[PDB]
Length: 281
Length: 49
Length: 50
Ligand SMILES: *[C@@H]1O[C@H](CO)[C@@H](O[C@@H]2O[C@H](CO)[C@@H](O)[C@H](O)[C@H]2NC(C)=O)[C@H](O)[C@H]1NC(C)=O
Ligand SMILES: *[C@@H]1O[C@H](CO)[C@@H](O)[C@H](O)[C@H]1NC(C)=O
Ligand SMILES: *[C@@H]1O[C@H](CO)[C@@H](O)[C@H](O)[C@H]1NC(C)=O
Ligand SMILES: *[C@@H]1O[C@H](CO)[C@@H](O)[C@H](O)[C@H]1NC(C)=O
Ligand SMILES: *[C@@H]1O[C@H](CO)[C@@H](O)[C@H](O)[C@H]1NC(C)=O
Ligand SMILES: *[C@@H]1O[C@H](CO)[C@@H](O)[C@H](O)[C@H]1NC(C)=O
Ligand SMILES: *[C@@H]1O[C@H](CO)[C@@H](O)[C@H](O)[C@H]1NC(C)=O
Ligand SMILES: *[C@@H]1O[C@H](CO)[C@@H](O)[C@H](O)[C@H]1NC(C)=O
Image (tube, rainbow over all chains, first blue to last red; front, side, top):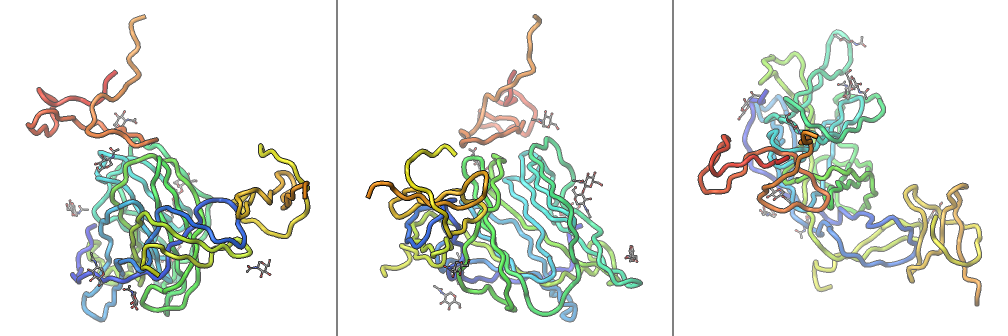
């Protein structure tokens, strides 16, 4: 499926006030100002804006926005959504079964992580279905890859139950991630906060905590994003099966080597920082 | 846990995150540690004054 | 007694590896300027050896 019935609009841009600070080590500190040098997202950097809006009253302005992006020394990722549309990512170089690649995805029951040789499709989406005879939402399709061979790393988590209702209103959850790849380790940091905004990236400060370090050991240059879409009695046809897709947006930034000054609270929480190369002050 | 020294141990009030084991001060010296068996926080103070 | 050939090693690569990284690709390596497009030949070599 290559998802026809799409418009073409120019990209949109934004900046990040003070987002992207993470804990540099695993040592407890209290009432101290500490200076470090590492890969950090520079303050007030240039951030590309992607969104998925599918209003049916505009006769086709529906857009999906899952392109291919480069991976230059780590990325910063943020998401604002209310209906659980973002699902995961794929990392690799050629993504054409001649090299290995990494997959992270959630399928409404459990999360899987795989380093395997994949033959990825051009439009790797998921899908949800809505029935009318009863009020319920269920998943129906999983179209990500064609084949998988030579498959080295594996991890599947314990089951859970997930809600798939298409809520109306404003955005409720903000989710942030930092990805890095050094010495054969894939490092992830995360932080979740609740918000009540509508159409922009909030400005503020939040510190990200370590989550996991995966020993995958691969060449990584490019990455995509995985999205879910809704289908119901809206003139099917698969490639143009009236696929209205919720509402969500996400943001991408790039890391660079910098020097920072970190402030540790009484209780070892990071509450402020200074970027030494932003301006002479 | 393989860290050697000498001092006096005393119960502490600071609380660690689940991924932290011991802490340092401005001089980068160890002043707190979590007991491996009973998950409690202890402080370390020098003996000579 | 006859000889064991199950163990393999790589012989040709375009660039050196980074620490703690692994590659298991089997693409044909080209030495001359003539393009390969598969089909090992005069200047095309199978990268792995036993
Ligand atoms: C979500 O993905 C998981 C992981 O593949 C699926 O769980 C596996 O399902 C297969 C087929 O029934 C079993 O052979 C495996 O044993 C399952 N994994 C585990 C760890 O038990 C799960 O079915 C998927 N769910 C949906 C809704 O697609
Ligand atoms: C989608 O477009 C690509 C473009 O190369 C094409 O190869 C593919 O066959 C198209 N759709 C599918 C899933 O067959
Ligand atoms: C960052 O974006 C905000 C929001 O419009 C703006 O007020 C501010 O001037 C921007 N900063 C820079 C350095 O562009
Ligand atoms: C940086 O952001 C500005 C603000 O709109 C934009 O005009 C410019 O194109 C961005 N830089 C790049 C390289 O796209
Ligand atoms: C709701 O109905 C669909 C088909 O219309 C069915 O597949 C699903 O199991 C039902 N869910 C219930 C009864 O909870
Ligand atoms: C990779 O896959 C090919 C074909 O699937 C196989 O011949 C080869 O032995 C595999 N290599 C490894 C290391 O699994
Ligand atoms: C540390 O936590 C305690 C509660 O356990 C709280 O009373 C105190 O104000 C906190 N100190 C800060 C926020 O630095
Ligand atoms: C990593 O990938 C790039 C892009 O294919 C390649 O040029 C580079 O040589 C690779 N790194 C190593 C160590 O081979």
